Image 1: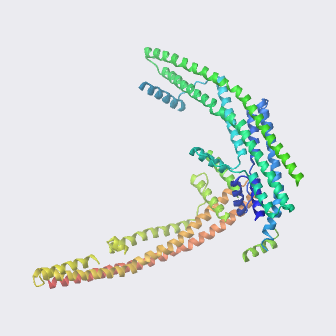
Image 2: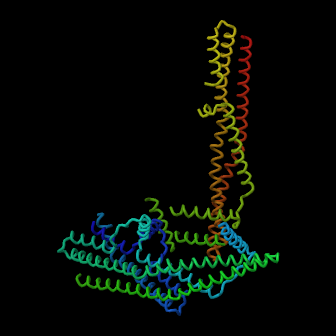
Length: 104
Length: 242
Length: 37
Length: 228
């Protein structure tokens, strides 16, 4: 009981958006790869960078916008890395146990 | 009062003929054209960043929809515990059930605490950012932009009148009527010029807007720094105990 | 025109919604197993 | 599963392009086209004739959905005759006329049974069988044609030679199924020829039924005249 609760909530913590999970479930049943959606940080970075470019790269405001966009994209990548590691060395074993030994 | 309807009629017919391409448009001064264009672009991007920021802060869209409903319903949206703190609660309860003496119990309970601390830190960032960033910008978009929009319409209307008068003079034959039209043309031109200055004056204020926003961005940054810094320290502490 | 671009976007989404072929022997076996189940 | 949805998407998109006229439409062979048209016409006309025949035999719509008018009139006449006095000449005539009116009603019921089972039934059977079966195959033939045209569109849009070669194979697959379905529908269309000959024999039966009805009714009226 406890193992199941923790395994689920921690997955929620990793993927906050419910619609995304629903899409994953559908694509899992569809047996087809779900599109590689861009995460919030990178998208925000893109918006900031493009906006800064439009206002003028030389301008201090533009410079800041571009810099922040770059950092934001870096953060997004790091986040993706974190998500991959957790599901590979944490969620996996627990799921294994609940799905195999428990049946026996 | 009926004369006003005639003015609305005149502005319309002219707008149609100009759209018909039969009539041309008196181009505005390049400076004002430039000023208006800059103000617009600014608003467009500022709006986009504000929205994407919000999404970043509150990932759950359904929650945002519920807030909108209660906002329109003029009711309070029930508060909810964030994912980090919730996980902590489940973990702590588990640890307790498995037995505090057991190392597994010790670890689970210890972690649940760190998670709740982290959740608290998260809410701090959300409030700090909202207070220091989103609002300042929102203000600008809701107030100054609106005013400028109104003035833009006034000048646009005046131009319509001017163009209509021109067209009327173009098709003026009777000397006396043509002279009256000349007086009418002078009349509209003056009013058009007056509004143009009014508009340019207001547009001048946009220059400071960029500087004001820059400060807000610097603040947001400081907030993120604060959030991660706290969380990092919290994590370190947890590993030491475990 | 604009309709064509909208159709292109629709097709892209269809692609969003929707391979090393294994040796025949294995494939045939896989099909057999599935049919049996 | 997902395959079902995918197939539908391809067919509809190609069809819309052809409807818009931007995309060309692969046509069918004249022989198959002629056969399909003949079958459609047969069902349309046969349907109308059978329905009107029902109205003619049973004018009452409610009765058609389900005592006949002649027999009801006969009842009224006989009752009146008794009240007016059976011995009275007026009473005598009313009673005799009512009886004959009921006999005519009986013959009408026989005609309805005889005709419907020898004329309406066969016409209905053809529409329920030959036409429907053809329509099902005709629909699948249109689906196969859409698949073929979609393959041709994919082929023309397959700039890559290897992709075009794959589209050629796909086109061949669609063509084979398309041609197969055409032949299946064609066989059903050939059956319509026999349907016409069968229908002709049924028409003759309906004619015979009407003649018997009129002949019997005439004799009944003759007898009443003599008695009165």
